[PDB]
Image: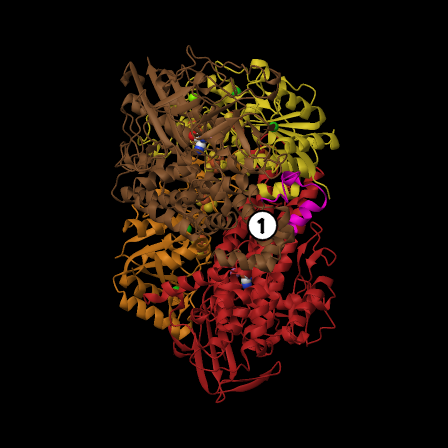
Chain colours: A red, B brown, C yellow, D orange
Amino acid sequence: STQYETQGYTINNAGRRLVVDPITRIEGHMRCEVNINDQNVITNAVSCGTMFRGLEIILQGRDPRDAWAFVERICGVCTGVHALASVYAIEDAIGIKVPDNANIIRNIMLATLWCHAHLVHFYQLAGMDWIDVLDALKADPRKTSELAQSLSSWPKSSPGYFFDVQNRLKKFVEGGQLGIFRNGYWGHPQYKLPPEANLMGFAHYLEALDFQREIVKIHAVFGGKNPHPNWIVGGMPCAINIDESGAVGAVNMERLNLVQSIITRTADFINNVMIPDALAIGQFNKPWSEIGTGLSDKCVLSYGAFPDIANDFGEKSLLMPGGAVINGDFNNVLPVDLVDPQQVQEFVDHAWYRYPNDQVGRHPFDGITDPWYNPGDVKGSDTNIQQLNEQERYSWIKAPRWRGNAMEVGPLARTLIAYHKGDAATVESVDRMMSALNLPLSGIQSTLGRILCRAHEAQWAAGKLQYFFDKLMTNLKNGNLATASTEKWEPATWPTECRGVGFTEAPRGALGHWAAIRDGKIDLYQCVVPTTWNASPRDPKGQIGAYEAALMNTKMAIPEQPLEILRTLHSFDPCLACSTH
Amino acid sequence: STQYETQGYTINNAGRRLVVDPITRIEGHMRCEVNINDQNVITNAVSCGTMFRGLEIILQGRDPRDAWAFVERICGVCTGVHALASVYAIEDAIGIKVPDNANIIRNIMLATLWCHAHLVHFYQLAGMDWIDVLDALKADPRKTSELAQSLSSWPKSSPGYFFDVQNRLKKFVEGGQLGIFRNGYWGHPQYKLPPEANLMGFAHYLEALDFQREIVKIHAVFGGKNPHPNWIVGGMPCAINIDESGAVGAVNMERLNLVQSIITRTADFINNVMIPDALAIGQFNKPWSEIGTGLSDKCVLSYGAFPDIANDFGEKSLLMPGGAVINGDFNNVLPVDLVDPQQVQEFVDHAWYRYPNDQVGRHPFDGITDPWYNPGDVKGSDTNIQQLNEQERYSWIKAPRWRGNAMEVGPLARTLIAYHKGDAATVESVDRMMSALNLPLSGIQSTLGRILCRAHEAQWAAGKLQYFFDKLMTNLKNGNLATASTEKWEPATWPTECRGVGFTEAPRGALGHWAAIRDGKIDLYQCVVPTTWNASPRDPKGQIGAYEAALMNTKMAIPEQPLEILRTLHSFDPCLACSTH
Amino acid sequence: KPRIPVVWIHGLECTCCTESFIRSAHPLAKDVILSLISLDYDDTLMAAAGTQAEEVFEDIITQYNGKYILAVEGNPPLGEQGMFCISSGRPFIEKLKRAAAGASAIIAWGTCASWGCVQAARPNPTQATPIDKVITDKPIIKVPGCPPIPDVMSAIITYMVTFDRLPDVDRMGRPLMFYGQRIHDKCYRRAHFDAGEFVQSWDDDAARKGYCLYKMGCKGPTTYNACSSTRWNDGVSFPIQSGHGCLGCAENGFWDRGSFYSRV
Amino acid sequence: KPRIPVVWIHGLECTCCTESFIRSAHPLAKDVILSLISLDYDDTLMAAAGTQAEEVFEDIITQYNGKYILAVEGNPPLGEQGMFCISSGRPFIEKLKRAAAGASAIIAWGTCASWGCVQAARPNPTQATPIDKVITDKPIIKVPGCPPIPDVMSAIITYMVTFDRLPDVDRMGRPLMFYGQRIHDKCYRRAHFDAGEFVQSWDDDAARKGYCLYKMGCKGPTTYNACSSTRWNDGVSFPIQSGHGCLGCAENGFWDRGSFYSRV
Ligand code: SF4
Ligand code: SF4
Ligand code: FCO
Ligand code: FCO
Ligand code: SF3
Ligand code: SF3
Ligand code: F3S
Ligand code: F3S
Ligand SMILES: [Cl-]
Ligand SMILES: [Cl-]
Ligand SMILES: [Cl-]
Ligand SMILES: [Cl-]
Ligand SMILES: [Mg+2]
Ligand SMILES: [Mg+2]
Ligand code: NI
Ligand code: NI
């Protein structure tokens, strides 16, 4: 065994090894291994992406106008965000400026995705880490009603409703066909909600499963379909016609009315179901405000998102702020430049790829994706892994760093950056949330805090949907209907050689696509995706990524039942197809 | 002034004359006049249909296959029922038998209409007679939630919900733009609900206004659109294809799944919102079990409906029983024959039509629709009716009689017929309903009883939707997909001369269409519609119809504010376009 | 912030346009009534009756003279001195003229108000006459169909409220947005029309594959509406999708253009 | 009564097909899971992870050997001895083969499982291979699209439950009900195609009237799916209706048929 120090942790792989493969209630394929000491405390954590497809290779030689459609298929859970980053990148390379309505619609597409992704994650992916579903069967329906009504104005709270939900669950499990609940962790000591709160949460799990389908109708109006809506280089394809013949063939008043109806419903659901449930989880699980901190009190990163001034990606335009904090110095939010070769770099010394020099990092404009499956001296064999060897290559995920630093990205990261840049709405929301829980601001830097920030962001994005909708309608009232710029659509108009960066904040964090065009074709296309950051393997200095750091020092009540590991990992909303692409 | 005796009433036109024109919260155009005595009790009542279009005249010369489309436009509130009666009448004339799926789908169309019509009438038309909307502003939201939760399992009951509803009402009213609530009867002493019940009822009014739109999606699937779906002579046009190429062009499993979703939601809403609200109205308004009896303890009529054996309109087939009671003799439910010239006859001695002899009644196969506006001495002029002259012609509605008797039709009539024929479900349901209200059976023969029967019927119809859907699915599982018979589609296949009767139970009561075909065209088309019965003017014997009878003997608290008149008239769900056609 | 006053009157009609309005999915009719307009008179929905209703009518058209929108459903009959449709003891046409005089603009809902509809079909026993032949000094927006599509009605309302102007119209006064193109120019069965792939009799193999309804009498080729694009009842269906040809119900005179089952 | 056991596994994929499934409007996915089937293994949704999840997988495939349906999303890579997709430390293909051996029938959801989809597009770095090239002794129903339509997925499921049989398929194993006709044979813009009325550049006047997208690269003429009839997201839209040509995403090899913006 070995032991070494990094980032304030002691990484020690002596002692008992635990393997969790597959990690479930994520997107895609992940393996996690830990070592635990005598005291059942994690002393080593190993994050492994167990899939690869190779979109960066597949994109070579394609027409840049088609790229969005390929890269959209990096992921169906964060559907749309890779298309957005793509059209941004290609427009940046070629020198295309889109009309204001296209930018507003793109912002609507992104905010819609934030609302959907954050909601579904909270209930369908993370919820069962916090809610004991089987313990819902012991609740009193009246006391469940009383609890729900103490927390929210949401209408659906009658004792008869909670009884009906509880009887549906009772019937579901009566034949012994427990389905998704089979062989769960129910009754684990870390389940702290009372029975009434379990039943309330389970009811809401079912309401959210139903309601989420409605949110994405906004994608269907502007983008044709969800999952995987359509986009174009130069704007959006959804031409608008309000008051002329043939409006039946375009985005018309009836289509805009449908969008408005969905916005209102989405905000209502988030504000009156998700938000109070997140706060209730907080109230009953306060110790988790001190577990899973990881890199969140050290190094956090946001590129920023939602340009409000069309084609301006600067600080005065981006509604979701960008910046970086390192060394725990939240008094110094640093600017990020995605062209600077000394800022974003990826390392592969611990990943299944070839570089000419694996002891250095490569900026994405110098990126290389040359897959090399070489797990080395595993316990087991190369096709039957019992234990990865984290002293050599152990993942399909490259290791991104910022100025050589290992960073956390995602809702907690963004919230910290915005808070410390002085964004008034962020400061107010965070202060009120932490006040309600009687926790210090540092309580947000934690597994519980990741969940609270996600709920905060869902409410923020639902409000922004209305803002963007209203901006679109203001343009339409002023006779500004344009949705595409086509003066540089044809390849003969492009530079013979050019490069660009497209960036945004996906639900899981900072996303960038770096593209080089030469002779009308993609010459290079490199993606660095939020879960690539968070699920990162180690670098040449042995520095650990956000997941490995968040798992360090965690106590486990029952080593064979990985509930604490799942709670922390799920708090980042891992997207493994994203991470590996 | 004069006085005479008929049907146990003393019809006396001495005393103050009150006029209500327009009657609102009905379909179409109605005027009502009454006389009240010195105790403010009604001693004379005059029902007047104030519109006519002449569909029976327009139908002459049409192709019989087209007739359904014209007569559907008799009414958009009971949309579809006239189309159903038309296709039944034309098929009866020609000798066409439809496939079982067509019959089942027609039954689904009719049950959908019953659900929709009964729900919208309860809330949007009649509800404000019983619920004091402005009084809802005085309710305690917590006591409203407690009340709702004591009556139903319906989920939407939180204090915050009722506060939000109340606050929306408050903001709506505060600027003085009271809309549909302006100059209402709010505060009248006959409003007996406590404020909490008024807020609950008002919340439900709004929920029903939203929900009703969903019910008619069943008509859209099978009939293309609602209002005014499409039909064919020979079956239905909605060809089915479950498992062959081109199912995208037909009623397929996805379409059927949509139907099933609507059925379940419809039953849920009716059973948990409308049914408890109807019973609550009964609990708080028991004296109305003794007001508005009219003809309901004397003479009631049903033709029957919902043939469950395709093409069989006999007693063993009809799921909704037919029959007639006269002279208050409910121990002898009599058979009805729509071809018998001594049974259904219409008189026009008190209506704006010409017959060769106005002292006799004409069976519809001998019917005549020759409009003749001749009001005699109103106080006023022919274009300024100050007081109708009920001693002569006073309405655009003909006067139907059954064996010379004046009859009531509709939900109460049907319920009495089924009960007294010994229908077990009806007997059990009615007995349990009156028991719950601690009222005798005779309490159903009243204005309150009409409302209670309508709610009961909505529940019955929602149940039958599922039964019919299941019957359709059984046929499809057995490979029986046929939806149309076309052997006699072509006019060359028809009899040179033939006649037929189409009958059903529309939401408002017994409906018949009598058609005669000659040389491939409609020679005669006569309709007798439920509101024609109920809103009937007098006949040569002076006998009064259901509305006039129901109003007789009623006490009014405040003569100038016709709340009691509205309550009783609305309990029949008047459809004046239907009545006059 | 005050809502625009609306007066909704009803002549000879079947009430289908009112029913269609309440089917609106987005915005809900509830939210139209509560938040977008002030529906200050409407016989189908209002609390007040009789003298109380007549007081509301008089008060609104006086208080808001020149500033309310008049919605009209149905039509006036000229026969029997107008007494085929009686409103407060007098011809409906008198109420129509009084309401029109104070309106800033008129919305003629449905084929009845726009053109005549079924009561005007041969032989027109009541001499039913469309609004624009009686009211000749006011802007009239025709929204035809029997009834018009629910979400078309509500989109037209939201357009006017949001943009503070009437929709642009064709030469017949129909909003270009929803009436600018033919049903047949946006019909999903057009591929079959073009291929000569037709239903010949009900429930034949062609019908079961969704072939074109032209030989069954579809009037889509001559009818302007949004049924084939926007569709009906929250996009659930439209006549042709459920297997019946278009009747032509948005077009003037559609009842008297021959049998629905005779070819265009 | 017991519900039919279903095992849902995931190879190389983006998870769009799972997301599509949960968008189902009728029946709701909730009701499918609670009432129609027994979704007994699914890494996306299940509570258990790691060893607990592996015990579920083993227990279900053993207890219900010969009796479960296997749903597959994604595909196996043949490159790097299969270790481009690793499950429980072993190649995913081994899990696929074990699951397939006990299944009564297999549903290949999406273009990944059916044909290959994006990871199989040139140069196919991982040697991603569709299910029917690995599993050669079991019925496989292909439900292609990227992803398939939500209510297509749920309609196929309800068909099988209700009728207790597999849907009838074409020669490629696609359900006839939803894949029997081309997009272009039920496209509402076909009138414009037939008239030569085409969008020529984005947001031109033609685009603003809903003209045909053929010249913008629409692949509808060679693509079999239900998008132009059933439509997407409870009937709200489809690619063409929102102004983008069909990519051809239900067809084998659609990524490598030239640019999406080159004509069919
Ligand atoms: S069904 Fe009617 S509208 Fe559609 S293509 Fe055929 S004729 Fe034209
Ligand atoms: S838009 Fe595409 S599918 Fe539709 S008609 Fe044109 S080419 Fe065919
Ligand atoms: N959110 C999201 Fe997906 C990841 N990681 C992207 O980009
Ligand atoms: N219901 C209804 Fe209409 C009436 N009266 C009919 O028929
Ligand atoms: Fe909508 S009232 Fe109904 S008949 Fe044709 S429009 Fe008229
Ligand atoms: Fe639905 S997993 Fe998404 S990529 Fe194309 S089908 Fe595959
Ligand atoms: S009949 Fe009318 S509803 Fe539309 S499809 Fe034809 S215009
Ligand atoms: S891209 Fe795919 S979603 Fe349908 S319209 Fe074309 S098959
Ligand atoms: Cl009126
Ligand atoms: Cl007309
Ligand atoms: Cl799997
Ligand atoms: Cl493929
Ligand atoms: Mg990369
Ligand atoms: Mg008649
Ligand atoms: Ni993702
Ligand atoms: Ni009616």
Residue toward you, D131 or B250 = B250
**Which quadrant of the view contains residue C82?**
top right
**Residue B308, image x and y in percent?**
29, 38
Q: Quadrant of ligand 9?
A: top right
Residue toward you, A27 or B488 = B488
Residue at the far bottom in the pictured view = A38
**Residue D12, image x and y in percent?**
42, 61
Q: Is residue B57 above or below residue A222?
A: above
For badge 1, the amino acid type reads: Asn
Magenta part of the protein: which range? B167-190
**Residue A557, image x and y in percent?**
48, 82
**Which quadrant of the view contains residue B231?**
top left
Q: Is residue D89 above or below residue B383?
A: below
Chain letter for the residue marked with disc 1 in the picture: B
Residue B531, magenta (yes or no): no
**Residue A50, image x and y in percent?**
45, 68
Left or right of residue B427, residue A106 in this image = right
Left or right of residue B498, residue D244 in this image = right
Dot 1 alpha-carbon crowd within 10 angstroms: few under 14, some 14 to 19, many 20 or more:
many
Residue toward you, A545 or C105 = C105
How many marks overall? 1
Residue toward you, B198 or A242 = B198
The quadrant of the picture occupied by the N terminus of chain B is top right
Q: Is residue A100 above or below residue A203?
A: above
Residue at the far top in the pictured view = B356
Residue on which the image places disc 1: B198
**Is residue C182 in view?**
no
The residue positioned 33% from the left and 67% from the top of the image is: A176
**Is residue A442 in view?**
yes
**Which quadrant of the view contains residue C170?**
top right
Secondary structure of residue under mark 1:
helix
The residue positioned 39% from the left and 15% from the top of the image is: B360
